Length: 90
Image: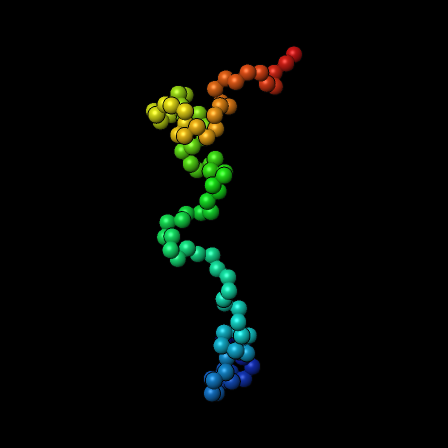
């Protein structure tokens, strides 16, 4: 049901375009979906949760939530308190 030349031919007995929908098959054999997990959200990045999880970053003593102690389970160690030197000279 796309074009039709003779404005009846797709009904005369049992015709539609070439076969059924359009040509024969282009509806199967690949999908995106979650039939058993109705709670997946967007693609998990389990070695790179650095933009979504409560892990990583100074949530510790200078953050805005009141928890203290490491971060969650010690993922990131240190990087945002003091450390040592860096990109500052004369």
